[PDB]
């Protein structure tokens, strides 16, 4: 037998985030997985990845430059954060 | 036997996010997976990926430049955040 | 037998984050895993990864430069933080 | 037998973070794992990783430079910190 | 038999962080592990890792330079710190 009980009875008004997982049993390889159920990515960067099998093999002249700059703003009040009977505000005077 | 019970009885007015998964049993390879059920991507960048098998193999002259700049703003009040009986506001005076 | 009981009875209005996992049994390899259920990535950078099998094999001339700069701001009030009967605010006078 | 009971009865309005895991039984290899259930990454950097099998094998001339600079600010009030019947604020006069 | 009871009865409004784990039984290798359940990484850097099998094997000329500098500020009020019936504030006059 295998029984899983989550949140059988609720009487009020809650704020919930539920994730239930029950299991019974060349260059990049991934198999038989679960990735990023409740996931947040903000300002994620990747430049070079898995270029090939034989890149720049013979007499390569490469100049690599990466500039991250400038005015960038990120304002968040609640992130993966449930609330109940509260007050949430973002004010920019 | 295999029984899974989630949120059998609800009496109020809640705010819920539910995700239930039950399982019974060349360059980039992925197989038999679950990816990004509740997923948020904001300002995600990727420049070079999986260029080929033999890229720039012989006598390549490459100049790579990546500039991230400028005025960019991201304002979010609630992200993956359920609420009940509350107040949410974004004000820009 | 295998029984798992989580949050059987609730009488108020709470704020919850629930994650339940029950299990019964070339270059980068990953198999049979669970990754990043409740995960937040902010300003994550990766430049070179898994370039290939034979990159820059013979007589390579490479100039690598990585500049991180500029005015960048990240303001967050609640991150993976549920609340109930409270006050949350982000104010920029 | 195997019984696990977590948070059977709740009478108030709490703020909770729950994670329950029950188990019954070339270059980088990982297998049969759980990684990053409640995980926060802020300003994480990686430059070179898993370049290949034979990179820069013969007569390589490499100039590597990594500059981290500039005005960058990160302001967070609550991180992985649930609260109840409280006051949370971020004020920038 | 194997019984585990955590937080059977709650009468007030607390702030909790719960993590329960019950178990019954080329270059970098990891297997059968649990890593980073409640984990925070701020300003974590890694430059070179797992370059390959035979990197820079013959007559390599390498100049490595790593500069960490610039005005960077990190301000956090509560980190992995739940609170109840309190006051939390970050003020920048």
Image (tube, coloured by chain):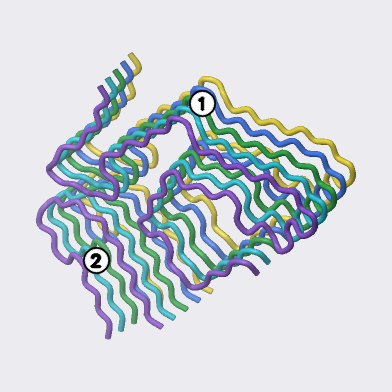
Chain colours: A blue, B yellow, C green, D cyan, E purple
Instruction: Find disc 1 in the rendering and name its residue.
Output: C70
Q: Residue at x 30, y 39 (%)?
A: E76
In this rendering, position of residue C72 left or right of residue A80:
right
Secondary structure category for the residue under label 2 = strand
Residue B23 showing in the rendered view: yes
Could you tell me residue C14's position as x and y percent? 21, 48
Extreme residue toward the right, this view: B58
Density class for disc 2 (Cα within 10 Å; few <14, some 14-19, many ≥20) is many
Tell me if residue A58 comes above or below residue B30 in the rendering: above
**Discs 2/1, front:** 1
- The location of residue B3, given as percent across then percent down, is 37, 71
Q: Are marks 2 and 1 in contact (CB under 8 Å)?
A: no
Residue lying at 50% horizontally and 76% vertically, measured from the top left = A25
Q: Residue furthest left?
A: E11
Measured along the vertical axis of the image, is residue A62 above or below residue A25?
Answer: above
Q: Quadrant of residue D83?
A: top left
Instruction: Please tell me which residue lies in front, C7 or A59.
Output: A59
Assign the N terminus of chain E to one quadrant of the image.
bottom left
Q: Residue furthest bottom?
A: E1
Q: Chain of mark 2?
A: D
Q: Count how many numbered circles sit on residues in the image.
A: 2
Q: CA distance from mark 2 to mark 1?
A: 47 Å
| Front in this rendered view, residue E78 or A24 | E78
**Chain at numbered mark 1:** C
Taking the spot 18% from the left edge, 44% from the top edge, the residue there is D84
Residue indicated by mark 2: D6
Toward the top, the furthest residue is B93
Compared with E74, C70 (above or below) is above
At 31% across and 75% down in the image, what residue appears?
C3
**Percent x, y for residue D1?**
30, 84
Query: Tag 1: Cα neighbours inside 10 Å, few (<14), some, or many (≥20)?
Result: many
Q: Quadrant of residue C87?
A: top left
């Amino acid at each position: 037998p295998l029984m899983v009980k989550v949140l059988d009875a609720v009487r009020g008004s809650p704020a919930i985030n539920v994730a239930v997982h029950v299991f019974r049993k060349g260059l990049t390889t991934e198999e038989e997985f679960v990735e990023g159920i409740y996931k947040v990515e903000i300002d994620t960067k990747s430049y070079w990845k898995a270029l090939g099998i034989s890149p720049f093999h013979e007499h390569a002249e490469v100049v690599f430059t990466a500039n991250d700059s400038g005015p960038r703003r990120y304002t968040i009040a609640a992130l993966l954060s449930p609330y109940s009977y509260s007050t949430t505000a973002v004010v920019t005077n």
